[PDB]
Image 1: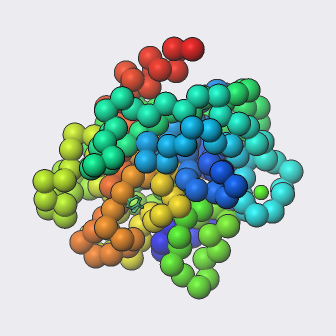
Image 2 (image 1 turned 60 degrees about the horizontal axis):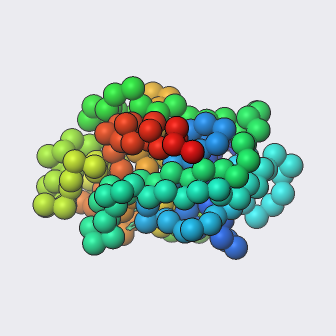
Image 3 (image 1 turned 30 degrees about the horizontal axis):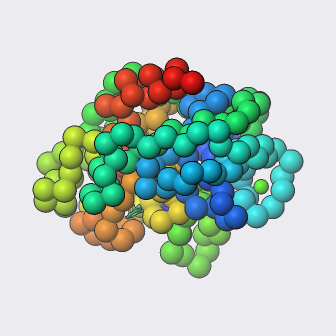
Length: 222
Ligand SMILES: NCCCc1ccccc1
Ligand SMILES: [Ca+2]
């Protein structure tokens, strides 16, 4: 996260770290058994770490749970990073408590201008901000016009832009798969962008609100 502030510890209890030796992507707990992340973060098996604040120090609030199933959206395309969403089933249910709580799936698509929070342990590109401690950032959802203008012909129905066209504040590598929460609901998943915090290059996010059918059906299928 570039240009944000350190999240208050456990203020984003749905935030999870996907670990394969080291943290490599974020994700969001949507219920005791399932985590939503980005398809470009796909790995056959991953260890989901919940209840984290500082990912390099044991705080006593963590739960490390291995994945049971990793399911990429059927239409995910590595050629253009389209339909960048994936579900991870936990091999054992997460224990919900003060440090671990699920985030609600959207009841509808958030309109442009809606203020959201994006968080993660990715590149901060600053000498002050320690990426081992969860970083937070408030970003507004941009209109399709603004999004298409920045990335001509690259924005599909499954993508939306959020951030600032002036740059300076953005999600970055390592934040991939993480949450974009607006009005208490998961509206986006950190997906792609040109660099981080560059003017004219806002972050691109998977549009969760158009995947409710797939999400609901898959979470009921085994
Ligand atoms: N806001 C940038 C998010 C990081 C990213 C960029 C390009 C491809 C994958 C992730
Ligand atoms: Ca920790």
